[PDB]
Image (cartoon, coloured by chain):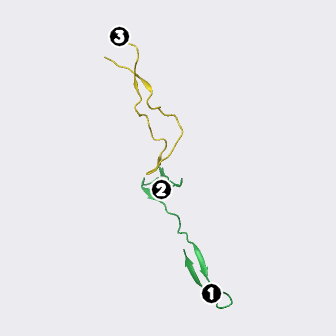
Amino acid sequence: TRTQLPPAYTNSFTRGVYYPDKVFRSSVLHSTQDLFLPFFSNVTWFHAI
Amino acid sequence: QFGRDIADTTDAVRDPQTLEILDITPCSFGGVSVITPGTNTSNQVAVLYQ
């Protein structure tokens, strides 16, 4: 009896940054290469109503 | 578990027994120089640590 409905979308407003290491760094600008969420990207929305 | 300085160097550490954070500073290093009056005059000299 559940109803099902096509996927919705929203936007990656600059979230998904996470600490890359267990090392303390402070007052510094530093760069890394890894898997990360691209900003401003179309991302899927779901609901249960 | 560690810290690092902007010189890419391990500045600080957590103790495994006390989980207390400790800061390191290298053993004292000194610049040395010597002053002379000229060997054809006298041999008393003064030393300067920079």
**Neighbourhood count class around disc 2 (C-alpha, 10 Å): few under 14, some 14–19, many 20 upward:** some
Name the chain letter of the residue that bears numbered label 3: A
Q: Secondary structure at mark 3?
A: loop
Relative to A26, is A14 above or below?
A: above
- Mark pair 2, 3: CA separation: 57 Å
Q: Colour of chain A?
A: yellow
* Tags 3 and 1 touching, CB below 8 Å: no
The quadrant of the image that shows the C terminus of chain B is bottom right
Q: Amino acid at mark 1?
A: Pro
- Mark pair 1, 2: CA separation: 46 Å
Query: Going 43% across and 51% down the picture, which residue do you hit?
Result: A27
> Which label number is shown at residue B12?
2
Q: Colour of chain B?
A: green
Q: Amino acid at mark 3?
A: Thr
- Mark pair 3, 1: CA separation: 100 Å
Query: Going 54% across and 39% down the picture, which residue do you hit?
Result: A33
Relative to B37, is B2 above or below?
A: above
Determine which residue is flagged by label 3. Answer: A3
Extreme-right residue of the structure: B40
Extreme-left residue of the structure: A49
> Which label number is shown at residue B37?
1
Name the chain letter of the residue that bears numbered label 1: B
Q: Amino acid at mark 2?
A: Ala
Q: Position of residue A36 (x, y in %)?
A: 49, 34
Which residue is at the front of the view, B38 or A26? B38
